[PDB]
Length: 49
Length: 50
Length: 49
Image (cartoon, rainbow over all chains, first blue to last red; front, side, top):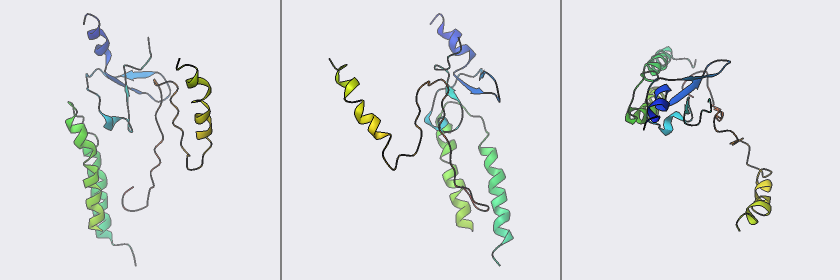
């Protein structure tokens, strides 16, 4: 819990900006299957250090 | 011969009214469930209209 | 003990699968960080897609 609030701080999800790196959303959302075939990724797999 | 502008006017309403629903940033997930399953009503109804 | 069969037998039945007819999509899974499938909607001048 001491550094989970540092992870979920930057964002639970993210999008990719046109030509460049990732863009983490400052929101804390729960994941759903409706988002899969549309936009975003589970940011717990976004592998930016 | 096969245009019917009255049916096409309604098609334009459905098109621009869809974006208002497909933009409303919601949270907590249950609206994300209904936010996707509303187009199966939003598009079905426009086909019934024609 | 599973390592023997899961490498030189269950791997032969996979290499054959990608060669069958009726299979026409790319379900690429290497690197979960950045993969999205392709949308192929059938569009019409009027009506809905």
